[PDB]
Image 1: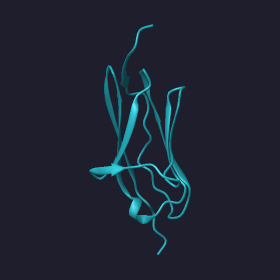
Image 2: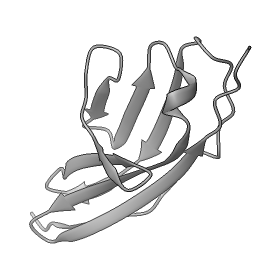
Image 3: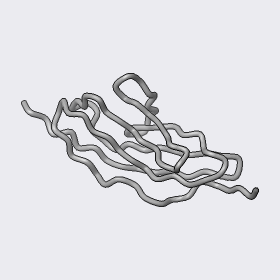
Length: 100
């Protein structure tokens, strides 16, 4: 039937995580058709990998995971969601608590 752009629903708060733990971020996302999504940190891009996993449910929930976080991963993360009808953009901070 009808379709439309991605929009805001819910974003995570500024996290603070002990060095070497598992952690995750979870962004609710609602647009039709299902948007393409890209990621950033401090003004440059972030690709996915085996420790930096990226998945999105058809139920409208995008997840961004850290298998083993390190002090160099700290900063302002962002992402952008795009479909044929429009664009939306989201931001969060990560304060990685070192153990030196």
